[PDB]
């Protein structure tokens, strides 16, 4: 099954973090990376005196069950990133999100796929569109139609 995974880092110096994350994704058993999007840049949320986000999408071929893949993305998040000590409930430094898992729809305590908000997020949709322009969501909606109708601004490359 092809899983699509979003990578997002908010480190002031995110490159090695993202490259290490890609290495780790490629080390996941029963899986291999099919392709990786370009690296994109998005602005911080709220105050602008914060670091930009580095965003990318990864297509991963896997024979793991969705929850098993989640185990690995969670592990990689723990091993390669951290919480902010002042805002521990907040976002981690490295985020790996399973955007799509084949054509599967999943709604469990641990896992919701497709990612619940991805259709509203250009920073997820554009890198995905670079590596899977013909993608159709499980509900039948076309990625091309979402980007076109909703008129997202494009993202700058990292
Ligand atoms: Cl869907």
Image (cartoon, rainbow, N blue to C red):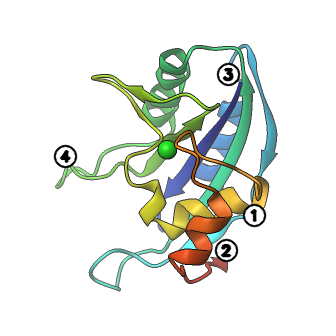
Q: Report if the CB atoms under discs 3 and 4 are less than 8 Å apart.
A: no
Residue 154 in picture, x, y percent from top left: 62, 81
Locate residue 70 relative to residue 62 in the image: left or right: left
Residue 58 in picture, x, y percent from top left: 69, 45
Residue corresponding to mark 1: 38
Residue visible at 27% across and 83% down?
47
Please identify, in this view, whether the residue under mark 1 or under mark 2 is nearer the observer. Answer: 1
Q: Secondary structure at mark 4?
A: loop
Q: Earlier in the sequence, mark 1 or mark 2?
A: 1
Q: Report if the CB atoms under discs 1 and 2 are less than 8 Å apart.
A: yes
Between the residue at mark 3 and the residue at mark 1, the CA separation in whole angstroms equals: 21 Å
Instruction: Classify 121 as above or below 58.
Output: below
Q: Earlier in the sequence, mark 3 or mark 4?
A: 3
Residue 67 in picture, x, y percent from top left: 47, 18
Camera-nearest residue between 63 and 36: 63
Which label number is shown at residue 89? 4
Total numbered circles: 4
Residue corresponding to mark 2: 158
Residue visible at 54% across and 81% down?
151
- Crowd rating for badge 4 (residues with CA inside 10 Å; few <14, some 14–19, many 20+): few
């Amino acid at each position: 099954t092809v899983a699509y995974i979003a990578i997002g880092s908010n480190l002031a110096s995110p490159l090695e973090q993202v490259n290490a994350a890609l290495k780790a994704l490629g080390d996941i058993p029963e899986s291999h990376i099919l392709t990786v999007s370009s690296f994109y840049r998005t602005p911080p949320l709220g105050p602008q005196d914060q670091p930009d986000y580095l965003n990318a999408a990864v297509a991963l071929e896997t024979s793991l069950a969705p929850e098993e893949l989640l185990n690995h993305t969670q592990r990689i998040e723990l091993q390669q990133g951290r919480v902010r000590k002042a805002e521990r409930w907040g976002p981690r430094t490295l985020a790996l999100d399973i955007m799509l898992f084949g054509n599967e729809v999943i709604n469990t305590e641990r896992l919701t796929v497709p990612h619940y908000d991805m259709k509203n997020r250009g920073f997820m949709l554009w890198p995905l569109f670079e590596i899977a322009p013909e993608l159709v969501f499980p509900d039948g909606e076309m990625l091309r139609q979402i980007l076109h109708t909703r008129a997202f601004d494009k993202l700058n490359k990292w």
